[PDB]
Amino acid sequence: MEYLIGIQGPDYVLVASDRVAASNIVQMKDDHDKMFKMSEKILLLCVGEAGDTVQFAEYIQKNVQLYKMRNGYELSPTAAANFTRRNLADCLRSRTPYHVNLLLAGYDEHEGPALYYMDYLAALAKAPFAAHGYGAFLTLSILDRYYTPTISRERAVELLRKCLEELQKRFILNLPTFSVRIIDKNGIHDLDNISF
Amino acid sequence: SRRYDSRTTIFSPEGRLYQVEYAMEAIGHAGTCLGILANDGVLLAAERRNIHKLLDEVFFSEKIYKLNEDMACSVAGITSDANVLTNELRLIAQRYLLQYQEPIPCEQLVTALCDIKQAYTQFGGKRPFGVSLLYIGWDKHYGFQLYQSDPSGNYGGWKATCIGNNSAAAVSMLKQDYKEGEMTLKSALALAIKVLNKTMDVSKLSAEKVEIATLTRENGKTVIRVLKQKEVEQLIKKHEEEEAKAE
Amino acid sequence: RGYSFSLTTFSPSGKLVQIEYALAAVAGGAPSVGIKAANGVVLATEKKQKSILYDERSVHKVEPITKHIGLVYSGMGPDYRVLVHRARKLAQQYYLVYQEPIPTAQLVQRVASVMQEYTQSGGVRPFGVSLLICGWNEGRPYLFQSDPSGAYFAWKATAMGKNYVNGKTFLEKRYNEDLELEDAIHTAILTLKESFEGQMTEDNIEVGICNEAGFRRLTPTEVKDYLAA
Amino acid sequence: SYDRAITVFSPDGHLFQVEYAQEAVKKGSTAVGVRGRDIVVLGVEKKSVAKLQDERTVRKICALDDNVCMAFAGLTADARIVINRARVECQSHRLTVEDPVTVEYITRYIASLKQRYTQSNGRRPFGISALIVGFDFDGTPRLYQTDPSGTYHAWKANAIGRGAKSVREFLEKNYTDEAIETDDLTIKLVIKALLEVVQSGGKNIELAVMRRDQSLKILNPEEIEKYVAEIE
Amino acid sequence: SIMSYNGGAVMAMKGKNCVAIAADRRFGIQAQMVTTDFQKIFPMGDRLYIGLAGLATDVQTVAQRLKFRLNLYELKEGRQIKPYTLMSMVANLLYEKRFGPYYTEPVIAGLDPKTFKPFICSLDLIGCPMVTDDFVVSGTCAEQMYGMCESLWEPNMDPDHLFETISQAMLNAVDRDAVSGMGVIVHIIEKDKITTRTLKARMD
Amino acid sequence: TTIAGVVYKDGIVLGADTRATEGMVVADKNCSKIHFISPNIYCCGAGTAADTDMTTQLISSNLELHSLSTGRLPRVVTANRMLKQMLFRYQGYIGAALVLGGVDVTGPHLYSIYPHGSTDKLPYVTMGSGSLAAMAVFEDKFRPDMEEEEAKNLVSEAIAAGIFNDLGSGSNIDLCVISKNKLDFLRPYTVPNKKGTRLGRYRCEKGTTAVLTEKITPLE
Amino acid sequence: RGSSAGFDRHITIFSPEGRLYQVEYAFKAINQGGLTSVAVRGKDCAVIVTQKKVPDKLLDSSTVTHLFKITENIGCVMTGMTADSRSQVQRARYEAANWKYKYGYEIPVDMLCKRIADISQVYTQNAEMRPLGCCMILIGIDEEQGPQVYKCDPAGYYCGFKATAAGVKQTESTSFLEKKVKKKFDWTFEQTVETAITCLSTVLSIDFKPSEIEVGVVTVENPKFRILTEAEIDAHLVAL
Amino acid sequence: TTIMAVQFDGGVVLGADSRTTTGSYIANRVTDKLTPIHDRIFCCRSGSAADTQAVADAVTYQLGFHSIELNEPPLVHTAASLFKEMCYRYREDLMAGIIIAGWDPQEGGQVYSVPMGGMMVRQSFAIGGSGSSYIYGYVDATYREGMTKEECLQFTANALALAMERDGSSGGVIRLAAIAESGVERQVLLGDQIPKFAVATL
Ligand SMILES: CC(C)C[C@@H](C=O)NC(=O)[C@H](CC(C)C)NC(=O)[C@H](CC(C)C)NC(=O)OCc1ccccc1
Ligand SMILES: CC(C)C[C@@H](C=O)NC(=O)[C@H](CC(C)C)NC(=O)[C@H](CC(C)C)NC(=O)OCc1ccccc1
């Protein structure tokens, strides 16, 4: 499967995603990006069935971008999370359902940083930290054991490293590189890829 | 049948939509409705047209309507069409709160209605809606806002505007009396009585002949309140006293 | 198919003449009166047949919509029969969802909506009928009027049809806020009597009353008693 | 569905409904667009200041996308409908091609819609003319005009709305490599062009600039006054 | 097993002139918890609330679609909804999906908007309303909740005793359900106040 | 569920148990299974509670619109035809087994409707999981043209048989009597079973429950 | 008085005085056929006598009729445009069938009249179609009201009557009946046929012969609609 | 279910058991499977109760309109054809075996078997239902041309009795009907009236 992680801090939201695209037993790409820029301060990390992730993610991205053009301002992280949930929930009982697990992360200059976990059934939950993938089973406890609400962005990257090192030792899938980005008042910032 | 068709959605030799212009003449014969934006809130002051003595007061207001928890509107023109447009405004607001889970921004609500109004002016073969609405509201993008829409589907934000009978005279007096950036709901609820006392040539404001609504933010909650007749009577009394003092 | 263009349009003076003409048909209708008292509402209408060859108990002008809501009219009875059916169907749609009798104000708004459609839809004329709806809800009596335009009004007392202006003047001088349905029934009969021309009889007039018990149409026999006094 | 033919040919081969639409554009405010070397400038006449009217709500210059923006003359309600259709189109293009729409691509679409409303049953032509201005990915400044007929052409500089002929005559004699070398000189060309029609001067003239690889910038009233004085 | 996918438990109890509504707080997939602060009880008026248990997507969707209809009704009718009308409204929404239903069973707890009389209720997943004068349970620990409320509920309980009963019934029932718990929230609705409390609960 | 119905000399007596069960657990200990279709017509319902409480409610609305237009009392044949013609177009997907009974201008009429659209006009009818216990009482004690008290005792005995012999049936016994002159809806007609008295006090006093947070919102 | 503005007299729209001229012209069509119909109700009988004019000896007279059976117990006499009349007879026959299929009992004559009048009203509110120029007088026996004579008109108006008339001599027939009914009603008795035969005979000054009139009757004893034969009609005509 | 119809020179005799069954339970023990589609045309219904009641109701409606429009008593073939039309069109959504027997002024007494699948066939005598199988050899051995209404009524009663005693899904009372120009005479055989046959002893 694919790995998504998000850690919300006091003034920032740190997100990481695996960079591998696999066909069956072969990795066809090790520089894949599973993060989509919905706004200047909103990111959607999407994993799931092939074809369903980009079809749903690109759709949500063009609709959030249409909002900015139509209204002159951008949708907030919470409005974007809810718009995504309605669309995923409104195609669930349809003949064209999207099998996608997502993590929306954004920073509102008023409500501050936010990380939202959503499953394929379209259940939205705001979380201090969350992960998607089979690797989440081996990493969510590391985050629960060390996550503190006032974590610094430096200590946040260190915990991100603890979780990805656990995946290298206990996970049965070769997830070698991870795309790491952070969001704050100054916008979305790409950080060095944690490779092993 | 081409013979019985009136062709409402067509241009005129001078690039004019006459059904829209005729509807606008209808709006100019309806009760004066004035809106004033203040730093502490927004107000709508309409002239009651149903003033018979055998009329029962069975509603919150006749001209003011709450469309959201943070937005309200007054109407000037055909009452039947206003009931249709107010119901559509309330659904557009609820449909947005469902998709995003946040209250609809005010200009977004006005644009949605004006898009429907403009569509009746371009295609369909049906008459336009003869109703001009004054919208008041508060959002977390621009704050207290007042807007006006026309049967053409053309809307605009205003600091103070009037629609209805003797509307032009009101806009003139508001233009020479409105102090942008220095208006408190007290001075706003004062210029309202002044303008109404001139637009409504029918004797002096009688409180039963006027309706006043205010939108304010109290403890992170937007509160829309139609001033009680006692409050309106006190306002009309103060205006009379002030005018006499200046005499 | 059918015409998809509005037959009602705005005149250069900003007026919809077709609705003005429908109100002319409502003013040429037989006189109707409504009085909201403190304990109920009385709806009285002049029902004078052209001959003695008409079964007066066959067709009714005062009709029940729900059990607390009743209606009367002035204008074209065929157009009224269409609005009575729609009022009943709208009233049942409310009960099927909220499982409670429809508020009289909600019924007047829903019926007024259908009437407004016939002023802006295509190939159709406005309804040539003004309606007087009486209802009892929340332990309060309600009296509302509905115009061919779709505009609804709440009244304490009102008159429609021929000699409605003189009737409203009579009601203005006679109506008292503190009245009982029995006193109200007398004033309503007196208002119709002022513009009747003939001998009001248990069959020349039709009266309906709404109270806490509900809406009902006073029997010719019951009306016979009121006309006696 | 109402399916009457509103736009029909007339003896002499004239679609009068389209000609009536252009009469509405001639009654519209004057919009001027000059295509420079590194800056495309669009300026509109703010007819009446109103004084009691929020300007943010009556802006006649809009951005269809990050690279494209348009000004209009004619009916403001018809324009809002066209701008929203073009904004949705630019996004649908980015989704099916993964690239920003080209200035002429969106000009072609806006024109094709403005044309179908002139040959479709139950519809009246749009009473608006637009000035789509942007920068192609190559970095070429682009200026196009659309007519209520659906006709579109590229221009070095044009003027739409009331006093278009007078302003275009001025731009015809004042447009040169000289009056376009400096971004400020390009801006003052649009300003002088409108001042030929605008009576108030400075107070009643909105203006916007879209430099390469930069968002649309709405010049503040003070900045406009600076150039208006320098242009005096 | 479509209701045990996300787990959940909601209970509403009547008192003397007071109502109570409690809910577990865990949000999980099968056996994995994702959050311990999920909302299952939503305000449907000043003294009216609805607790939703079932698929969490359906809990959120049914709440949002109910608010759409409630806000429209409140603005049009110009009055607050009475507890019984909200139940009739939820039944209509749920039965409109009879062949393909929302996997959520709702409990309504509130005081009449005028008489301030206690009203509690429960609806099925296809909208079958059952008004009770004691308690109403809904979730994956319903049997445990039935046994606790049948042995602890007393008539005419005061606001404080209602809190001690709904709280004890919820804590001992969710402690025998593996997919329910991770916290308990309780709203005591009275005429002049709404006290909300979070209980110390087993986080295992 | 034990819903039953008998036709006596002056009219019809309908009866029902009051238990609703979700699985093998009781959900409602006082459900109403007799429904008003019209002032002269009532319908006992068995099967899916939501289906039997919506098919009846829709037919009551349609017979009301019919009676307002006709100005005449509804005929039990109209309800049967409306109910059967709807249950048929749903092919048993709407599980509503009903005992329709009423007195019209043609006399008293009792009918049985099945979820697929089949109807049966009979002098005595039983439906629900307690139908055969109730039928045994009717096939053993029913006599043509009985009196109200005799016919009421029969329908209560049939409902008791289902309550004490069926596990999906129990609680109280409701009886609806309909004559040309009277409609008597005896909701709690007989309360045959009651909860035993509590022998120990398990009330928790203030302070037993430890709270982590509290927020009191004052209401105006 | 007769003010007109627009297509007030071409399509069904209100005149400056709210009159609807098109419906008024549809009542002039009923009198274009030239025949008059009379219907009287008695204590236990309802009779519909109509005038039969077989213009040519080449036309089969068995086909020239205005009396129709909507249902075994509901009968109709149609006056006005023949083709419009056969159209409403068919709509009545279908509405009566749909009624028994959906409700399980025969439609009351009042209910058939209201349905037909409701369809007629839609022709008065829509401009795509002309109103039908025909009047339907229905007769039946109600189980709780006995003899019932109902008439619907091209405007959507329906009413029950003790005795009615439609056609060219509607007014004169009304007056004739509006004097017998006043004295003691259409002398109740199956011989109420004499009142109808004499009403049509007097207004259309003519001593009808057994073949110049058609008589339909419904009775409490025999509730089924029946068209009397020339011999039966001759018996009544000879009696008077 | 046992349904049977026979034609005689002047009319037709029809017969049926009176048992409705849900599994092995008798929901109705006095059912009327002989339904009148018109004055002198009846149907004998077998198979699904809801399906047979719906089709018979529909044909009575269509046949009623046809008779009032074509001012003439309906033909038995027309009723059989309308039954065939629906039963063939919805053969995959309808379990309904029907016997349309009645008297018409033109073709006399006619018995038509519209079996399951939608097929239609005129027959001197017709049988149908689950009990039809046990009396095939009897009807083939006891039927004689030239029988009368009285002999035909005995044939139907004797045959239905034998089938009701061997088929568990058949039983109750034997409902008989005789249709002729004169009218329709209906008869119910119950208890000792129902024909009896001695059992063995060995
Ligand atoms: C009026 C009666 C129909 C009410 C009562 C009597 O049968 N209902 C019942 O006994 C049935 C039991 C079942 C074996 C039919 N129970 C129910 O119908 C309960 C309603 C109670 C919880 C209030 N709801 C229920 O279980 O429905 C679940 C369901 C959902 C979709 C389709 C079918 C069934
Ligand atoms: C056509 C009628 C005369 C019925 C006749 C059949 O020939 N007699 C019967 O016994 C037939 C047997 C059939 C399945 C072969 N019975 C039936 O068809 C029964 C009758 C119902 C009223 C219970 N129908 C049936 O089993 O499904 C309907 C149903 C729906 C819900 C519960 C129980 C039964």
Image (cartoon, coloured by chain):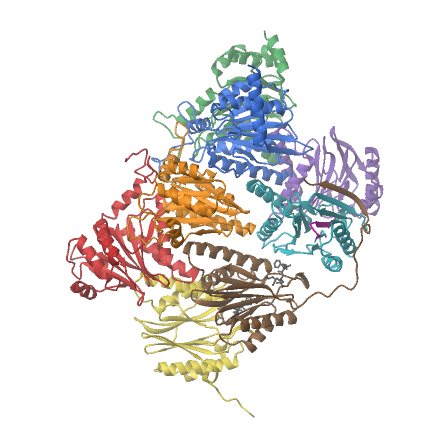
Chain colours: A purple, B blue, C orange, D green, E cyan, F brown, G red, H yellow
Look at the picture and state if H144 lies above or below F147. Answer: below
Considering only vertical position in the picture, is F70 above or below A132? below
* Residue E143 place in picture, x, y as percent: 73, 59
| The quarter of the displayed image where residue D61 is located | top right
Between H174 and D210, the residue placed more toward the observer is H174
Residue E114 vs residue G57: left or right? Answer: right
Image coords of residue A66 (percent x, y): 61, 33
Q: Main secondary structure of the magenta part?
A: strand
Give F103 or H18, whichever is nearer the viewer.
F103
**In this rendering, would B217 be left or right of H116?**
right
The percent position of residue E163, horizontal first and vertical second, equals: 76, 50
Considering every residue shown, the one lying at the far bottom of the view is H202
Can the viewer see residue B191? Answer: yes
Question: Which residue appears farthest toward the front when viewing the image?
Answer: C229
Q: Which quadrant holds the C terminus of chain A?
A: top right
Q: Which residues are drawn in magenta?
A: E14-24
Expressed as whole percent of the image width and height from the top left, the position of residue F124 reads 52, 71
Q: Nearer the viewer, residue A123 or C136?
A: C136
Residue C26 as seen in the image, left or right of residue F166: left
Q: Please tell me how many numbered marks the rendered image carries.
A: 0
Magenta residue check for C172: no
Q: Is residue E21 magenta?
A: yes
Tell me, yes or no, if residue D56 can be seen here: no
F120, above or below D79, in the image: below
